[PDB]
Structures are given as C-alpha cells and as structure tokens.
Image (cartoon, coloured by chain):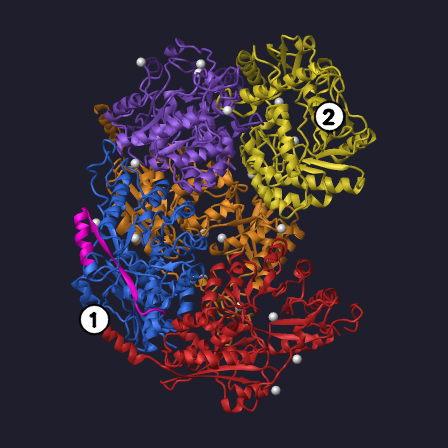
Chain colours: A yellow, B purple, C orange, D blue, E red
Amino acid sequence: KNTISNIECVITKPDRHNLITVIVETESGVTGYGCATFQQRPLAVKTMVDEYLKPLLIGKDANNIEDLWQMMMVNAYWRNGPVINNAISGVDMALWDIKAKIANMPLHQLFGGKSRDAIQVYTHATSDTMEGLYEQVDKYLEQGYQHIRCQLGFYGGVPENIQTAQNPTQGSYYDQDQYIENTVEMFKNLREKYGKQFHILHDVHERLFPNQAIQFAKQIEQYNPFFIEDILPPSQTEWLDNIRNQSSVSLALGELFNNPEEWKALIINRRVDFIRCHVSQIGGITPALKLGHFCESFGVRIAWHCPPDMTPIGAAVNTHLNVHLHNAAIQEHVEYKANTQRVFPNAAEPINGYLYASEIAGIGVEMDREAAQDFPVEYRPHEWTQSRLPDGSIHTP
Amino acid sequence: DLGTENLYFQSMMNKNTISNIECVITKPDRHNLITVIVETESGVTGYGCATFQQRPLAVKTMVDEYLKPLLIGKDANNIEDLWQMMMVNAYWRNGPVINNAISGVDMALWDIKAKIANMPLHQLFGGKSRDAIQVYTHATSDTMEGLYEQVDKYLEQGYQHIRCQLGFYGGVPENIQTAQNPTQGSYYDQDQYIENTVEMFKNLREKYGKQFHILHDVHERLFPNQAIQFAKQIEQYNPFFIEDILPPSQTEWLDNIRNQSSVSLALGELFNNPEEWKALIINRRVDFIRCHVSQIGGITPALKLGHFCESFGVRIAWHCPPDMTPIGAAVNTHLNVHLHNAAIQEHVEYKANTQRVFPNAAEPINGYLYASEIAGIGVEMDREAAQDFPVEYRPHEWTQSRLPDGSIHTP
Amino acid sequence: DLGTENLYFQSMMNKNTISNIECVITKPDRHNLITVIVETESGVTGYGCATFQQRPLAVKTMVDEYLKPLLIGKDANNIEDLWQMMMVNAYWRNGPVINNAISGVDMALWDIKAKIANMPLHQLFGGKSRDAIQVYTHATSDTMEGLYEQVDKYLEQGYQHIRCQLGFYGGVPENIQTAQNPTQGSYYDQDQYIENTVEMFKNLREKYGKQFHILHDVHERLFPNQAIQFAKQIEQYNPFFIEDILPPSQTEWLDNIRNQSSVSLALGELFNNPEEWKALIINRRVDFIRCHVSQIGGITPALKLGHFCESFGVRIAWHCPPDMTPIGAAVNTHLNVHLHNAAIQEHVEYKANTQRVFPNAAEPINGYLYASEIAGIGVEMDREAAQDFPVEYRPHEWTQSRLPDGSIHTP
Amino acid sequence: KNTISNIECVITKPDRHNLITVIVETESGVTGYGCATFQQRPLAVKTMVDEYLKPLLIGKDANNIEDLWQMMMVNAYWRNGPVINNAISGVDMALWDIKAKIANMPLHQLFGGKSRDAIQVYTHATSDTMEGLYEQVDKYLEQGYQHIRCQLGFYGGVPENIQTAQNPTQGSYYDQDQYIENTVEMFKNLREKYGKQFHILHDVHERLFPNQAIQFAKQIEQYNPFFIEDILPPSQTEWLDNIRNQSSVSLALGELFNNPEEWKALIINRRVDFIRCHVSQIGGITPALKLGHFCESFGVRIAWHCPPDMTPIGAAVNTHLNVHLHNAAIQEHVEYKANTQRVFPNAAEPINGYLYASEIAGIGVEMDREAAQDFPVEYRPHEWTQSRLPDGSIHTP
Amino acid sequence: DLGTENLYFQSMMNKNTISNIECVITKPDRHNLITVIVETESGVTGYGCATFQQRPLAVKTMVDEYLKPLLIGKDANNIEDLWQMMMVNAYWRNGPVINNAISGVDMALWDIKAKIANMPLHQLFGGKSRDAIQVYTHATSDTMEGLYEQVDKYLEQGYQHIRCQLGFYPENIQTAQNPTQGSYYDQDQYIENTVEMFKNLREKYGKQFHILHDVHERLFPNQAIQFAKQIEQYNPFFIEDILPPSQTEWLDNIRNQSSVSLALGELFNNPEEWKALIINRRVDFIRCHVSQIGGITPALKLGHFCESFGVRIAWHCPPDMTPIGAAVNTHLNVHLHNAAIQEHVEYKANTQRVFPNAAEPINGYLYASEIAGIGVEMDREAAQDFPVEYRPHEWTQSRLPDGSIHTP
Ligand SMILES: [Cl-]
Ligand SMILES: [Cl-]
Ligand SMILES: [Cl-]
Ligand SMILES: [Cl-]
Ligand SMILES: [Cl-]
Ligand SMILES: [Cl-]
Ligand SMILES: [Cl-]
Ligand SMILES: [Cl-]
Ligand SMILES: [Cl-]
Ligand SMILES: [Cl-]
Ligand SMILES: [Cl-]
Ligand SMILES: [Cl-]
Ligand SMILES: [Cl-]
Ligand SMILES: [Cl-]
Ligand SMILES: [Mg+2]
Ligand SMILES: [Mg+2]
Ligand SMILES: [Mg+2]
Ligand SMILES: [Mg+2]
Ligand SMILES: [Mg+2]
Ligand code: NA
C-alpha cells in the first residue's frame, strides 16, 4: 500500500519547446516522473494537474494504477481530449515509474520483458533544396540510420509565389499542388541518387484533401516509402478505403488521436499499417499497452509519435514500450540539445540506427528540478497552425 | 484591380474588430458556471456559455492565456473562419476543455452578429420553423408516492413530458454486498437499478396511463447485455426516450437493440468529438441526438450537426442540465425554434441567485419554452452580480461511481 | 400567460408580411431567365432566381397561380417554415418545376432578411471562411489549336482552372455510320468523343504541363463500361475533376471506378430529389457535389446540403451555367465564400444585354470571384430593362441526343 | 407510320377534384386519351402539355411509344418530378390507347393478355366514430368487398383538443399520439366485432416520425392488416429496415414517388410488400410496366394508387395493368359520381369485390369533350397540406 | 351480374382457342433446329423457336407428349397466364428441355397475337426505341492471316464489330501417358494466343473496329483475372463468358481491379443464375439465349430488370437457332432501349429454304421485320427434306492436359 503524498506539474522550456513533467511523491519515499507534454497549451495542462488531479489523488494507493487510470478518466464526467488526457498521462507514467522502482526493474521488464533487442530509429531530413537534403541524408547514413523521413521544401509563412485573393487574410499559406509536385520530385531524386540504400519516410501532415491524397498515393507507391504519414486528417480516414483498394502504399496515421473512436474503425478495417499515437495524448502507458495489444490482433504495427515537443522521460517510456510490445516497429527520434540534456539527464540517443531501453530501475530518466527552474514557460503563438490555402481557407495544419 | 480594392475597402468599413475577451466563472447556486464575454471596437458586446462545470479553471486558463491573444484584433464578422481557425489552433483538438472555451467565443460572436443585425438569434439563422419548443422536466424520488407528487405538480403546470427516476444511485454501499473493505467511491447495484426502473414504468402507466410522455435517463449505468435486456423490459411502456442506455464507446451495441426492440433512444450529451456521433447517426442507432452544445464547440457546429441529423431523420434534444448558464439555455431555445428537426428542450427551474446573475432567463409556460424576441441571444450576465459568487472547488464525488465489487463504471 | 402574450406581440412588431409575389421571364441574350420578386409591407423587396430555362412558362404558372395566393399575408421572416411548408404544399413534391418556383421565393426571402439585417447575404450565414472563391471558365473548340488559343487567353486573364472540351457533339450524323434512314435528332459517337477527349488531355499536358488545372464535362454521354474505361484512360493526366461521368440513375456504377481509379469526380447538376445525392455522398462516390441551387429548392436546402457534404469530406462546386440569372450567381458566390467546404465557382462572361437587365453582376478578377459587400444578395433585376426582352420559345434540339443506331441517350 | 396531328390538355372538375386529360390526335384519324391528373397543380401540367409537349410531338410517329417516352423524359434536360411526369403520362397513355385501337384489342391484350380473371378491390371506410365506421363497413361487406381500408377519426383543421403554443401558426393541426391511440383502438374494435370476416387496410399517410412508426408497427402487427400504407415518408424509407428486422407487419408504400431513386433501394432490399406508385406520377404506362417487372423479380407486389383525384381513364388503365401484370395484387377504388360519369362515360365499377378490365378496343374509356367544358378548372387551396404538429411544425402531409 | 357476363361475352367472342401443337426438328445445314407450330380456331398459325440443338428429341418429346395435351383448348390470347401456367406445370421447373419447349409455344403465341393485331412483333411491345440494331459477326481461324482475311471481308461489308477467335493451328500438349479420350486444349496456350491476337489486331487495324472475344468458360478464376488485366489495354467491346455460370462471384475480383468490358449468360436457364449477377453489376452485357430462359415473355421482363441496373443486352444468336428465333431477337433488339448489339452468322441456302425471308445484316445493321407477326415462318414441306440427324458434339467432352473435364 503506497499512499500518494504530493502531485506537482512543472513546465520547462530548456530549448525550443514548452515541456511538461508531472511529479508524484509517495509516503514510501519513492518518486515518479511522467510526461504530460501538450506544448501548445501547457498552462491548461498544469491547471488541470494542480487544481484537479492533485486533490483527487493525494491519499490514494499508488499501487493500483489500473483503477486510478479508470477512475481519473471519468472523473470530470466529460472525458477524452488533449488537456485531460495529458494531465492523466503524466500521472499514469509517474505511477508506472514508481512501481518499476519499487520492483527494482526497468519499466519494460515490469511489462513482461523484451521481445526485441532494441528498436530501430528514424530521424528527420528537411530542407528547401535537394542539395540541403543530400547533405543531411549523407550525414545520417554515416551515423548508421537506415530510415530517414525526408521533406523537400517548407510549407507556410507569407504567400510569396502563391496566387491568393487580392487581400489575403493573415495566416501561414501553402499550395497543395506545389507541395505534391515537390514531394514527388523529392522521391524521384532520392531513389535515383540513393537507390535502395535506405528506407524513405514522408509526413503529409494532413495537408491534402481526399482526392489529392488518393492521387498522391498513386504517384509515390512505386518508390516504396517505409510509410506515408497522416495522408489524411483524423476526421476523413474512411477515405482510406479508396486508397487501400487500389494502392500498395504503406500508411501511418494517428499522432493527433485523443479519443478511441478515432482509431477503432481505422484498425479494425486495416486502413493503416502503423499506428502513430502520441502516448500522452491517449492518456499514458496504461492505454498505450492496451492499444498495442488491440493493434497486434489486427496485424497493425506501432510507431508512437516522438516529436521534439516531448520530454526525454516520454521518449524513454516509448523505448520501454517499443522493446516490449512485439508489434512495435520503429521509433522516431530528434537529437537533444545541451539545455534539454541538463534538465533531463541520461536521455538515451540512438546508436547505429537503434535505441536501447534504459536498464536501471524505473523509466530511467527523471527531471532535475533545480535546472528546470532556470527555464520557465514562455508563451509561443505557434503561427503555423493558422494554415491557409491560396483562397484564404483554413486547412487542418 | 481597383474595383476589387474598393470592395475590400467596403468589407473593412463593416468590420467589427475584437477588442477584448474575458472569461468569468460564477457559482450563484449549486454549479460553477462559465461565461465568455467578447467586446468589439464598435462597442457591441457578446456573451457565450463555456460551461464545463467539473473543470472550470482549466476552461478559464484556456480562454485567458490562449484564445484571448489569438483573437484580439480579428474581425468578429467572420464567425465561420474564426471557428475553423480556433478548432485547429493548438494542433491537437476536440475535447471538453478546448471545445468549451471555443464555444464561449463562438456563442458570443453570434450574439454580436445578431445584435448588429438587430434581430433575435433564431431570425439570423433563417427564422422559426415552430411556434415554440416543447419542454420536459425532471421528477426524482426514493419512493413511488414521492414521484407521483412531483409528477402531479408538473402536470398541473402543463408539462406533457416528464423525465422520471425512481431511487437514488450512489454514496456508501449500505444495502450492497461488496468485498470486505470496499474501495472509497459512490456505490450502486445495476440489478437493483434495473428492477426499480422497470417497476417505476409499470406503476406510472398503471396510475397515469397515456396522460403524459415518460422519459428516463440510464446515465451509462449499464453493461451492454443489461442494456439489451432493459430495452426489452420497458419497450411495452413506450418511453418518449430512453437516454444514454450505453456509454459513448459502446454504441455499436445499439445495433443489437435496434434489431429487436421498438424502444425509442436518445444519446450524446457526452460527445466532444465528431467520430463519436457520425456512425451513430449514419446507422440510425438513436432517435434523438443529445449533444451538449458547448461540448461540441458552440452554435457553429450545432447548426451543422442539426442539418446532418436532419438528412438521416434523427431529431434533436440538446442537453440542458442545471450546469449551464441561462445564456446557453437561451441559445438552445433559439436553435430549437429554428431547426426543423428539433424535438424537445430539457429544463430545470432557475433559482433566485442564478436569476440575479443572468436576468431575463426564460421559464417554460404550459410546457413550452419561447425564444427571446429582442436583438441578440437575449440573455446576458450581470458582471457585478457574478462577482459576488466566485468559483468554489467541488469534488463531484458521484463521478467515482463503483459497482459492488469495487470497480469503476462510467458515471 | 400575459408575459408570453407580450413576447408574441413583440414578434408581430418585427414581422415582415409578404404583400406581393411576381415572376418575370426575360431573355436578354441566349437563355430564357427567370426571376421571382417578393414585396413586403415594410417596403423591402427581394429578388431570387427560378431559372429552369427549358420550361420557363411552367415555372411562371407555378409561381403566379399557386405560390402567390399561398404566400400573400405570410411572415417573410420565417424562411425555414415557409420553405418546409412550400415543399410539401402540393403533396407530390421535388422535381424541377416546383423546386425552381420555390427557389425563386426562398432566395428572395433571404435577400429580404439580409437587407433588413443591413448585411451582405454571406454575413447573415455566419460570415466568410475564405477571402474569395476560385473560378473556372470554359474553353471549347473543334481543333486543338483553337483550344490553345482560348486557353492562352484565359491564362493571361489569370484563370488557374479551365474546363476544356475538344470537338462538338450533336447535330446531323455527318461522319457517323447510322441506320439507313436515321430518326431525327442530335447525333454523336461515343467512341469518337472518348478518343478526342483522351487526346485532348494528352496534348494539353504536353503543351502546358502543370500550368493550370484541367476540368472536363462528360455530360452523361457514356454508358458505364465506357465511363470506367475513360477514367482509367485519363487518370494519369490528373484532371481537377471529371464531371457527370454517368447519369444520375447509374451512380452506383461509380463504385467500380472508385475501387480502381484515382480520378477526381464531380456530379449532381441534374439532381432535384434528395434521394439522388444521399447514397452518392454517404459512400463518397464523388469528390465534388455539383447541384444547381435553384433545382434543389434554393438557399435553404443548399446550406443543409453543404453541411451534409462537409461531414463526409465532400466539397462543393455549385452548377453556374449561362442559363441562370446573375442573381443566382451572386447567391452562389455568397454561399461559396461562407461554406468552408466550397471549392470553386464555374463562370461564363455576361453579355451586355444581360448586364443591362441585372446591373452590378460580378465578374472574376485574376481567377477569383468576390462576394458582394452591400446589403442583401447585391444584384437585382431592372424590371423595365427586363421587359424589352420577353420570353421566346426555344426547342433545345440538343436534348434529343441520339447514338448512331438512332437511340436516345441521356443528353 | 402514324403521325401525331394534335395534342390537347383539358382540365375538368365535374365533382370535387380538378382532373386532367390529354388528347392525342393522329393523321390516321385515331384518337387517344390519357390521364395527367396532378390535382394540386393542374394549370402547371396544362402549361407543360400546351407550351412544350405539343410543339415537340406534332409531326412525330405515334407508333414508337418507347422512343417517344425516352425522348420526352430527357427533353428538358432536367427531368423527373410531378409536373413533367404527369404531362408525359397523359401523352404516353394516349399513345397506348391509339396503339390498342389500331390493333383492335383491349389495352391489356396488347401487353400479353390476362394473368388473372379480374383484380380484387378495396374501398374506404372513414368516420370520426366507430359507429360511423361500422355502418360503412357493413354496407361494403354487403356489396361483397373483402378488403376495406379503415380510418377512425379525422386529422387536421383547427387545434381544438390539442396543446399548442399560445398563438399557433395557421395550419391544419393533428396530434400523432392521438392518431396512434385511435388507430390501435380502431383495429382492436374491428377485430373484436368482425374477426377475420374481411381484410383490414390502413393508411398512415406519412403522419409519423420513424420511432413512432416502429412502435405502431409493433402495436398493430397482431391484427394482421392486409397492409399498412405509407408508414414513413419517402425520404425516410431506410428506417424500414428497423421494422422489417423485428415485425411481421405487411407494408405498402410509394404513391408519392416520381423519381426512380425513391423506389430502387426500397424494392431491392424488400423493405415493402406492395408498391403503391401513382402511374401518372412515374410517367405513364411505359414505366409502369417496367416497374411491375422489376418488382416481380424481387417478389414485391403491386397496388397502384387509385384515388378520387384521377380520371376514370386512369382507373381503366390501372385495371388493364392489374389483370395483366402477374404480381398485381389489388386495386383501390372510390365510387364515381354522376357528373364524373357524364364526362367519362362507361367507367367500370367493382362487382362483388372485383374490377374487370374493359374488353373493347383501346383503354375503353374516353372523355366527352362537350361535357367537360361544363366543368372548368376551379382553384382549390388544399389546406390539409399545411399539416402542423402541436408545436406548430410542418410535418409531411 | 349482367354487365360482367356481358364483359365475359365480349372476351369469349374474342378468345382464340388453341387447336393444335406441333414440333418439327429440321437439319438443313450443320445444326438440328427445332420449331414449334401453334394452330388456333382463328385459323391464325404461329411459329416459335425451341432450339436446344444438343438434345432435340427431348424437346420434341416434351412438346408432343406434355405441352400439347395441356394446351389444346386454351385461349391463346392470354400469353402471360399460359406462360406462368406452363412454367410450373411439371412442378419441378426451369432447365433447358422444359424452357425450350415452352419458348417455342410462347414465341408462337406472340406471333399469333401480332398477326391478329396486324402489327410487326416489336410494335406490339410498344414500338422502336432505335432504327435498327448494330451487328457483330464471327472471325475464326487457326492463323492470324486467316483472321486478317475474314476481318478485311467483314470491314468491306460494313461491319463495325467483329468477334475474333484464334484457335490452335492432343498432339502437341503434355498429357499423361494414356490420355482419356476427349477434346484436349491447353489454357496457357489459349491465353497466350489470344493476348497476341489482340495485340496484332490493334497494331494492324488500330481503332477501325470493335473487337469482341468469347472465352467460352475455358479458364479457371485465377486465369480469368490474369487475362482481364492482360487484355484490358486493348479495350475489347466485350469479353464474353470469362467464367462459367457457377463461378460468377469471382467476377468481383475482376470488377475491383480491371476496366475490362464483360458479357455473360448464354448458358442461363434459371433466374437464380442472373439476379445477383445483375444486381451487383458483375457484367456489362447480359447474353441469355431467349429460348433457354423460356421465350419472349421472360426476355421482356429480364430486359426491363437489366435496364434498371444499367446492364445492356446482347442476346445469344448462334448458328444453332432458327431464323425465327433470330427475327424475334431483332424485334426485341429494336424495342428494348437497353439492347446493344446482335450477334449474327450468315445463313446457308438450305436454311434459307426452310425458313424463307430471314433477314441479313445491311451495312452493319439488322432491321426488324415490318410485316405482321414475327415475319419468318417455317416451310414445313421443305423442312421434312432435312430430318433430324444424331450428332455427338465431341467438343463438349473438353479436357485439360491431365485428362480432367473442364466446362466446355
Ligand atoms: Cl511561433
Ligand atoms: Cl485554395
Ligand atoms: Cl430560489
Ligand atoms: Cl460534490
Ligand atoms: Cl456528488
Ligand atoms: Cl460488481
Ligand atoms: Cl456583349
Ligand atoms: Cl435551340
Ligand atoms: Cl440546340
Ligand atoms: Cl449505337
Ligand atoms: Cl381545400
Ligand atoms: Cl409537436
Ligand atoms: Cl449456302
Ligand atoms: Cl460432332
Ligand atoms: Mg507527424
Ligand atoms: Mg443525461
Ligand atoms: Mg455540367
Ligand atoms: Mg395513400
Ligand atoms: Mg458465347
Ligand atoms: Na481495386
């Protein structure tokens, strides 16, 4: 019986992103750390943890993670969504951290142990020129990456070479046909230069309307991308059937999900090959395990969302999940910077294309509380989310 | 092109630039209520409901820290752009906290547009498609006789529809066989609830026959096999609707019910993601949609959802609980007299403190709620009154709903 | 209840009683155009489009003899009730004659409401969700070079989308192997049409590459096996859309296409019954809905259909042919800047006679149509100008479309 | 080769209804008569015939009914709907009348002859009291009817015993629950008094919302009605699946149809037992034959709509169709009055529960042109179509 | 009741009582043909086609021993009732022998009705919806140059559609040691010859004419699917009988991934064979042999059923059919709006003698007869110079290299 004695939520911005950590203290003296990172609205997550989860949780038994999760999820009656789920996730991860520490085992060992030696990793190559891409690709290949997500061009900002209306509404503009043309050209160039040296990934980032997605799938399937990610927004995934009926292209989707109705039909109908959920968005380790299991039955594999806007605690959690879950496929990775490494010591980095799970007791990564205070929250507008098409229409960003 | 430039100039002339956004939490009676206020350079002020009573400070953080700096300086006229833009602004989206904050703004923008048009809100929409909306109220008691007393009172007031509940479900497990040291929570027994409710319907029909329409809210208390059995048990009593017979995540089990029972079904007060309702409606799994307008992001998506339902022949009974501002209720009445497929409006009487903070809140008359006829929504918040009643923490222990073995059930 | 009585009194005060209904047919240029005019006691006049060019006198009989005595004395404010009531008023319903007559009234009532609100029509709806709508125009010629000439002209004007057609299809069967004494009609050969069109796409892409979006209207010329083959033949050329690849009665054959071709599809200009579009959209058989707004009964059902399409991710390209008043076109532009899922507006230049009868008709500027910014729809009919151009009988011989063996095909 | 020399459209109102007849003259001297009756909008039908069908048709070969039908149907480009279809129907029926006359055969013999001796008939018993119903039922039983459509109560007019809003909008009001209660009570009374002496039919006339229709189906299925008609409006027939899945009630629908999309899914999915199309509403004899054939394949039977608002020419056409089409089931009938019999001589009336097809050349019933002029068109508002529910909402009438 | 009896008198005065039923098998040329003749008290005689060439004595037995005593005395006017009655008369129903026998009577009854009406058959139906029906003919050879020679001839005659078959030139196939007797073929060789045939024709003639090809149920489903993808680029007007009637659900696998135009149904004699096929749009043309489904009466209904689903009609018109049957199909083809094309093979002189006035295509079109009735009858004295003769039809014992029977 391990009574929860305190709950804290710290927002820290060591580098580019507002990061959110939840800290759970227990009377047994064991402390857990969890990721609650919803970078766009961090003060709302912190309010949720401080004003609501904390008085709910203090005095309750930390051992019973499953009950505390089921209870937390329905506690406000209305449920699901990014603010509640991230707050819960931070607590849930911290609770698993504590249980693993008390067991004196690495997190993935609690789960049932390894089903692979380490998880393969992909990184990001992004440039406004092919030469910029080549330079980044060559570097990553030298470091031993076998999977690289490639993007030609940047899409947003002022509408310079775009035929807008005469007085366009303020926003971040792009042209879907330009994006398609550039991306197809990128794939053609890369295959001509590198052949089958590495797996090419690409993130469509819900930029397209359904008919454009179906066309794009047909234009790039010959290049056998390891996956094409978020080819459609979450509200339109039924359109995937048109693609699956006539194209061999490998698809990944789901980083935006925070309600189970978003993924069930998707997986039951085998509309994607990889699920890309952001663990903290779906409510933490507890539901991530069940989702991995649900996918496994249908033969869908796992590529959890691992963006720079996530703590290294969250990344370590994902690696524990990835070496355990038999249907885990690959882990997204972006290099950490000095400030972030200082606030979150011992964060693992890929080695020759692989990320290895921590082997000490717990998640294996905590937050240095003193170092975090050197980097308070800082407001950012995130102007790219005001994504507009040439006619001035908002499109899903 | 000069002509095009002139047309834009003319657009700028009729602009209503947002000058301020505020979020007030107020608790005049039992519930923490949330109002968003939007001011414009033209001096026209809008009021909207952002009420998520269980997490009000999170909604207020959302409005104050994020929606405000996003919206100041923008043209209030273009509600549709502002809604589409607000909905995706955090990238991750949907959910009760963001949707309520957005609803508060959306409703206030519609209020502003209607005031500038000098019309009641429903007239902006396209006008009335009914004279007024029928209303149901709530009768709840731990005895059948206590229920009859409340029923008799409402029938005398002219209500023709009453949501009836026999028994109270929650609290300490007094007459429930739990494990030896039950986990702290609000306990109930599903079988006792089913038994009490079936008996309630039987007794009401014996006593009142066809005098009034009987509604009942299952409130996601049941597992699917219990739901299917219950539908067969009470279908003979022809409820006007049986509400939330299953939680949002299990609505595919409604097919089993629709295939074998004639029972009339309502669902959806918990929805805050469109994936929750699309399959539900497309497959005609319910007869009434019950969404909470602020939970789905305001008037803008409510109109669309109304129209979507209408094509499938599904009707509308928006959620109108005590935990909603009278502003939200007035908005619902405007939507209800306008949308042709609206069916009925839930109502609970306002207490004096609430009436003080929100003057002119409409009450049903002979079983009908009438839409406001002055410009705008027609109901505002008294800001000075509101501040006498600041937010106050409530745990809402009923949401820790436990079954006899100590497990959580959807509350 | 006195308070309720006062509220009704207040409703009566803001009433706009219909005082007159008129229907004018006018033919300033090539087409018989139809405008409905609605007057109110308040002195506010509305204008709407009721254009069914092939049967204008039937539409006028419908307005003058039936809708007029039905509507005089009724409150114009309640567009939604008036629409629901008009739609069922003859018992039998739907169809091009009744829908157009109703559309004329519905659009004029919306015009009146917007004028009384002192807002542009799109602002009544909820405001803009785009700055302006993109526009495509028509290029048609019997030679590839003649097509390039028209294309070059439109590209210079800033169009980014052009509907292209190579060859003309109809008239006497000059180079067609018919039976010995072919029945009188407008003859064409499906295979020659397919061959010409495929070559047209190939040549345009070779000449212009990705410079502009290519549209093409199949105009229900084909049998389903021809449609499926054609989709596979031109999908590589990525048309912006292929329009009416099948007649309305054969759209289930679109599944065969959707399952094997990436081709972008548009359909629906012929619809005047909701059963024609529901399955189409629910099953995502097209990418753009193409309904003719007056054919489906006006702005009121157009808004609903827009919203319905939006939930399924289907976008909107309302039919905007020469046989429609500039009033109808302005209405379409208002719907297009408002509805978030609107995609593009078809446009053909107005001739001087037409401009005289309908002053202030908007023209595209650099490939965009901008919504009017004055109160109302923004475009009216000049009644004195209109009468210089009375109805004139036209047979429309192209609708007697025959295949080489002499059989009728959907025209 | 039989050239069309003239086309005329006469509206006549010998009794209660504006009736519409189309007359086609041919150079061979043979004259055809057809029904185009859309009683609510007769001047629009007449305009359509006079101003559009006539100049299209004069000079064309009357023999080729199939081509003339296909051609007429698409002639305005936009198509289907009650005004165009009724005008076409009048011409189509008149063309078949001419062909039968030239063949010197009764219409049904042209078709392929009889597949039954005569068609069974039902009539209408309607009263605001049960005693009124009993009196009408007893009469019809005595005349040898074995099928009677029964209705208790009248639904419309001023809202006397209805709880409306305080100032209800002008219209024709009814209460759906009152209607259901009365109708169930009617069935119970009739079965108690008459047992299985006759088949009971009832017309719901689209008065109900879907959940009310499903309930009503369950409340009356025990009474084994011969059919329940129009239990739902045409836009909601997909709801019939809920009924068909759980109720044995026999259903009829379709009098409102004037677009084939309205009936195809209905019949393919066996959602009704009888189709009730109004022949002139679907465009005449030509499409009625095809529809009968289409239904036959699916096992759906035919009860063509035969209301008082139809010429006796139209009724005779329906009897010719009914003795020919093997899946025809029953013919609705209402007695003709003196004025109507004068304008349309020799109209057949049921005999001992049966209607017999005409046996002279042609349809067998024509219009007396002189007698029709004594009864010009007269405007009627048809106020019942402004049908409102207690809250003042329009409902499908 | 008086008025009803008076109606019953007028009907009686117009009744046309069947007085005799006859069935003649005749073999003027290559095929045993079957004609039913119905006589009436009117003195009006009708002729119909009952041709099931492989089993003609069974059909004749069916007519002479069973339909004849059933029909004598009954009113010929009521074709619909007599059809419904005949179809269920042996309780067990459907099938090629019963349906052909019934078809002969049915067509003959329509012939009589049209003669009494003094109208061409198609005019009874409601008249023309086209001027004439386009025609395809048969080009068959064991060499490409033989094919070219026939194609060139037909093109000069004005045909725009040609069914092309390139056959083999079990002596060259790898069978087992002592192959069971039968008519052997190799599916892979057939597929290869056919693909190369299409390729050559398009190379040589481009889009000069529409190419049709009859697979004649020779393939397994995986081979049918492959073949569809192999020839779809050549845009055949239709590929006929790509699968046997029992395996048509496999057509979905084709429809989901190929644009190939398909026709099927000449083998059908039971409605259950075509309903799902049409409801699910699994073919583009229905190919039913009219006498196999039981005559004009059900052909009219089937055409209407097809029309609703957008399926078009190409009735089976082989050489093993009377010219009476062919004329009936042309009447059906000029009337039904969804009729597409009529198969035709040239009549030889003996057949012309037995069936005078049989129409031939003119410039790629067949014109419906314009006299009263079907327009073609059998000359009974000439028919008896050509009595039935037994033929084994050894091609129906169709075997694969391993000795297995395959659908022929
Ligand atoms: Cl930023
Ligand atoms: Cl755009
Ligand atoms: Cl109080
Ligand atoms: Cl509480
Ligand atoms: Cl509580
Ligand atoms: Cl339990
Ligand atoms: Cl000009
Ligand atoms: Cl013309
Ligand atoms: Cl023309
Ligand atoms: Cl043709
Ligand atoms: Cl009346
Ligand atoms: Cl009501
Ligand atoms: Cl010869
Ligand atoms: Cl042989
Ligand atoms: Mg991504
Ligand atoms: Mg509830
Ligand atoms: Mg078009
Ligand atoms: Mg009826
Ligand atoms: Mg064959
Ligand atoms: Na496919």
> In the picture shown, does residue A272 fall above or below D305?
above
Q: x and y percent of residue E72 in the render?
A: 39, 81
Q: Quadrant of the C terminus of chain A?
A: top right
Mark 2 is on which residue type?
Gly
Mark 1 is on which residue type?
Asp
Q: x and y percent of residue D223 in the render?
A: 30, 49
Q: x and y percent of residue B362 in the render?
A: 31, 23
Label 2 belongs to which residue?
A: A113
> Which mark is on residue E1?
1
Nearest to the observer: residue C65 or residue D392: D392
Cα distance, mark 2 to mark 1? Answer: 94 Å
Q: Given the image, what chain letter belongs to the residue carrying mark 1?
A: E
Q: Which residues are magenta?
A: D115-140
Residue A31, image quadrant = top right
Count the marks. 2
Residue D216, image quadrant = top left
